[PDB]
Image (spheres, coloured by chain):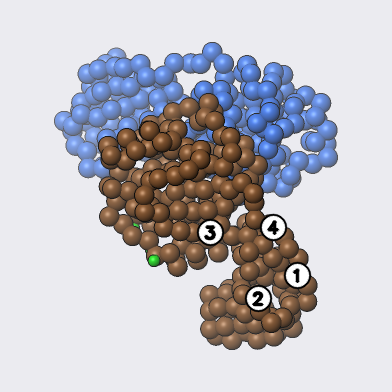
Chain colours: A brown, B blue
């Protein structure tokens, strides 16, 4: 049971080139009943009409609201770094029920991110996890926040299980080359700080928090 | 800075062809200073004396105790299933401070494993992670247990009582059979992508037991 992604309007869902290729791979055809999401919490049961090289369109039969906006958000600051790390962190954020991703370039990174690429990673992950309401993605200029913030310092574990998790939480995943001293002063003074393989620490940290917050 | 695995005897560490080959891949030569572990908690700083095709030997210069046996053990029963899953679970056991790994072929698996092959996975993961006291591996013929055993189907694991030595039963890819669901309820405490779930669950337990 595959879940496609498109834009609903005027009784149809329209699909971009990327989706049409994915449908040709599953070898669908005109007449087939399919399920799409718009990424804002809705599910559409549709009959495929057109499948062409760079586009497709299906007629909507049924809509179900599958997920509503949460009252308390889980936010993660993802460092703009080597693509393999960045793609991983974004995928895990979809997976672990994060509501908002914020991309920050820490002082020791010279990387950039394409926000359109990040949205594709979110889309493809969500289609796999059957997540109807996609996390939002934004740039973040400054390490300035409100509410409860937890910082994952990758170069040191601190006590995660002692941390207070009351209310809305932002988790700040640290950069590969480490916080500069300016960043560290800024984050010690404003957040709560908490050695394993990068991929394991990130899953365990964000995943424990999501668990406790019942985001998963 | 690599870490090799060898056998310590009378002032030298000897190494097998797997390690010798690895030494050649990383361009080591006779006369270089290397670090080895025995897999028993100790680090050995040695001078590499002989690097041959099938074997190597180094002279011990310094020995440091890195890791001791814990009072309270964390054991995990790993299903014998598709290699890619089994290998991942072995490596996470190494990395998350599990002390002992027991392989069980559940009823809906038809797979088999050689302990020699599992040990190689342990070795290579432990070399990579710089774990000096390697976990032990063995077969578990029956799902028959004593002690705190908790049975996992990859939430409110957060409420599980994890005190004392503990065994964690990770279920098979095809699910527990009826007989298995009954058997496990008679002797255990029943408490996302597979890899994510496996890390979050075993990691949380390890972290709560302070094994990491
Ligand atoms: Cl890159
Ligand atoms: Cl990019
Ligand atoms: Cl951009
Ligand atoms: Cl980075
Ligand atoms: Cl299995
Ligand atoms: Cl071995």
Tell me, yes or no, whether the two marked residues, 3 and 4, touch with CB atoms within 8 Å.
no
Which residue is most to the left? Answer: B31
Determine whether A199 is above or below B143 in the image.
below
Q: Secondary structure at mark 3?
A: strand
Tell me, yes or no, whether the two marked residues, 1 and 3, touch with CB atoms within 8 Å.
no
Mark 4, other Cα within 10 Å: few <14 / some 14–19 / many ≥20: some
Q: Earlier in the sequence, mark 3 or mark 4?
A: 4
Q: Which mark is residue A136?
A: 3
Instruction: Give the Cα distance between marks 3 and 2.
Output: 18 Å
Q: Which mark is residue B44?
A: none
Q: Secondary structure at mark 1?
A: strand
Q: Which residue is mark 2?
A: A8
Q: Which residue is mark 4?
A: A67
Identify the image quadrant of the N terminus of chain B.
top left
Please provide percent x and percent y for residue B111: 65, 45
Q: Earlier in the sequence, mark 1 or mark 3?
A: 1
Tell me, yes or no, whether the two marked residues, 3 and 2, touch with CB atoms within 8 Å.
no
Q: Nearest the camera: A129 or A21?
A: A129
Q: Earlier in the sequence, mark 4 or mark 2?
A: 2
* A207 relative position to B188: left or right: left
Instruction: Give the Cα distance between marks 4 and 2.
Output: 16 Å
Q: Earlier in the sequence, mark 3 or mark 2?
A: 2
Tell me, yes or no, whether the two marked residues, 1 and 2, touch with CB atoms within 8 Å.
yes
Determine whether A70 is above or below A165 in the image.
below
Q: Nearest the camera: A169 or A122?
A: A169
């Amino acid at each position: 049971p595959h879940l496609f992604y498109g834009t609903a309007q005027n009784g149809e869902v329209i699909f971009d080139e990327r989706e049409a290729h994915h449908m040709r791979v599953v070898r669908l055809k005109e007449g087939d009943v399919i399920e799409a999401t718009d990424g804002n919490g809705f599910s559409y049961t549709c009959i495929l009409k057109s499948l062409k090289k760079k586009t497709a369109a299906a007629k909507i039969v049924k809509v179900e609201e599958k997920e509503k906006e949460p009252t308390e958000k889980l936010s993660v600051v993802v460092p703009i770094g080597r693509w393999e790390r960045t793609r991983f962190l974004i995928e895990k954020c979809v997976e672990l029920g994060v509501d908002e991703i914020f991309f920050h370039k820490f002082e020791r990174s010279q990387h950039e991110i394409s926000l359109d690429k990040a949205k594709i990673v979110v889309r493809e992950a969500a289609k796999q996890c059957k997540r109807y309401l996609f996390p939002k993605v934004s740039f973040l200029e400054k390490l300035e926040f409100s509410g409860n913030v937890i910082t994952l310092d990758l170069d040191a574990s601190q006590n995660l299980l002692d941390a207070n998790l009351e209310g809305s939480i932002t988790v700040v995943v640290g950069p590969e080359g480490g916080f500069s001293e300016k960043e560290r002063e800024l984050l010690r003074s404003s957040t709560t700080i908490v050695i394993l393989r990068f991929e394991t620490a990130a899953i365990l940290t964000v995943g424990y928090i999501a668990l406790k917050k019942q985001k998963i």
